[PDB]
Image (tube, coloured by chain):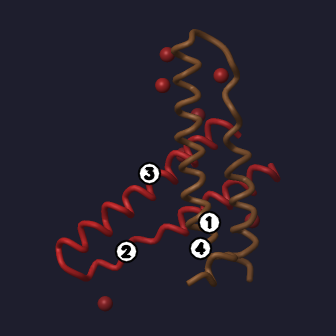
Chain colours: A brown, B red
Amino acid sequence: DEDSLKAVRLIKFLYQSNPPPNPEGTRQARRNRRRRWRERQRQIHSISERIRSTYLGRSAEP
Amino acid sequence: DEDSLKAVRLIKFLYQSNPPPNPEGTRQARRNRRRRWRERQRQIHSISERIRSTY
Ligand SMILES: [Br-]
Ligand SMILES: [Br-]
Ligand SMILES: [Br-]
Ligand SMILES: [Br-]
Ligand SMILES: [Br-]
Ligand SMILES: [Br-]
Ligand SMILES: [Br-]
């Protein structure tokens, strides 16, 4: 019943730790930062889904 | 350092969430579980190293 609390907090915390990049520099840099941000967001997605499926609401799911 | 301890706790919990796979099985099934697990680890490394730098 305590793993559930960590799980909800971790997920919360995961998304907050990935703010969008500040627009600055050349087109090439700005594109580079946005590509990396997107990669990180997807990673945060799969991680979260894994956590939800393990510790939370999706864990009851067949 | 309240917020910092919180962060490290969540990260620790995160590593906790990716236990190594049971080793038993064919070399093929073992190679696949290991590959997938390796991927999860890297994701976690990114996040954590990312949070270290930015927190
Ligand atoms: Br916590
Ligand atoms: Br941008
Ligand atoms: Br660049
Ligand atoms: Br690109
Ligand atoms: Br066994
Ligand atoms: Br680190
Ligand atoms: Br650093």
Task: Read off the residue under disc 2.
Answer: B21
For badge 3, the amino acid type reads Arg
Mark 4 and mark 1: Cα distance apart in space? 15 Å
Q: Do the dots labelled 4 and 3 sit on one chain? A: no
Task: Give the foreground label among 1 and 2.
Answer: 2
x then y, percent, for residue B13? 62, 65
- What label sits on residue A6 in the rendered view? none
Task: Read off the residue under disc 3.
Answer: B42
Q: Return the disc, 2 or 3, that comes first in the chain's sequence.
A: 2
Decide if ligand 5 comes within 8 Å of the CB at mark 2.
Answer: no
Q: Nearer the viewer, residue B43 or B54?
A: B43
Q: Is residue B25 left or right of residue B10?
A: left
Q: Given the current orientation, which residue lies at the most extreme top position?
A: A26
For badge 2, the amino acid type reads Pro
- What label sits on residue A53 in the rendered view? 4
Helix, strand or loop at label 4? It is helix
Mark 4 and mark 3: Cα distance apart in space? 19 Å
Task: Read off the residue under disc 1.
Answer: B13
Please tell me in which quarter of the rendered image ligand 5 is found.
Answer: bottom left
Task: Give the foreground label among 1 and 3.
Answer: 3
x then y, percent, for residue B1? 80, 49
Mark 2 and mark 3: Cα distance apart in space? 15 Å
